[PDB]
Each structure stands twice: as structure tokens, then as C-alpha cells.
Length: 118
Image (tube, rainbow, N blue to C red; front, side, top):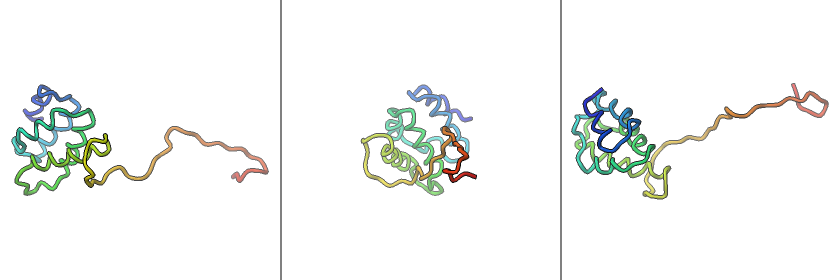
């Protein structure tokens, strides 16, 4: 991993967040200090899902010649909340399809003259 794994654990944030953050600091996706104190502060008070949401998109952001990764990260945190609570803006984003598998239910059969069986 990277040295920045352990700061997160001590800054207030759970392991389950840092486990999904270390990857970013190893992929070549950041320059270790690609963020600023202001982007840290808005990344102390989150819930369990919160940071995971923000870290996800950030791994797939258009970063190739960004000048300020902090602006990007302090952006995405202010949209995902729309699927979390009534505490954000109407911003755009593109997640959570249609579609839903059964996976918990079962079928039936009843051979009789009244039923469209095979």
C-alpha cells in the first residue's frame, strides 16, 4: 500500500474507508498532496457510505490534466448525498439503473386442465 493509509484511521475515519482509498494512492491517480486542508475537512464528517461514494467516482474522474484534484473531490461529495438524505442540491449524476433480480423467491407448478402448464 502507501504511507497515507494510516493517517485516515487516525484523522477520524474508519478502516473500510481507507481500504478503498489506499488504492488511489498506488494507482498513480494522485500526487500524495493532490488535495488541500479544505478537502480534508469536508472528508472528516461523513457516514459509512459517504466517503465510499466520493472515492468511487474520483477513481473514474477526468483527472488527466486537472490542476486541482481538491476542487474535483469537493465537487462530487456535494451530489451523491442526493441518494443519502434531503441535505444537498439538485446536481446531475448517473448511477443506479433499472433492473432487480428475484434471488429470494420461488416458483410453483400445478398440472391441471385449468393451468397454462408445460
